[PDB]
Image (cartoon, rainbow over all chains, first blue to last red; front, side, top):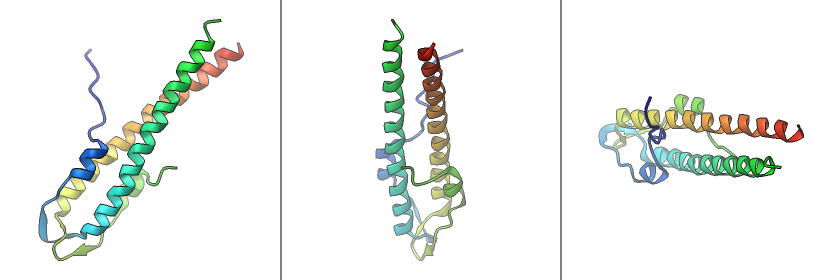
Amino acid sequence: SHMLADKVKLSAKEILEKEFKTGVRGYKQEDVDKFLDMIIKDYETFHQEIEELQQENLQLKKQLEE
Amino acid sequence: KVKLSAKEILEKEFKTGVRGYKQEDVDKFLDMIIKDYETFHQEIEELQQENLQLKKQLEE
């Protein structure tokens, strides 16, 4: 019945800031950090997409008052 | 446009070095990110849906 949490768990800031423990062997850091950059780009790209579809749907409703 | 899919993040196999990141910690975080990708797409699809339903109502 209740309020909707911001359903997105992370932000672009939090991804960039995240620090991981190391082991005597694990994922090569440079490859993980690069992959995380692609992801950050996608997060930015998704918000812009949403922002635009919201504005475009608000535009369309203004036109419907007539 | 978009540079990754869920499927690509799921399937990615990093190289391992001698003092690399803990693999468990990275998977758990990647796993969070994947669920966010999913959330983003639903959000978009329902605004795409609504977008098309408003273009119909405007031609009528």
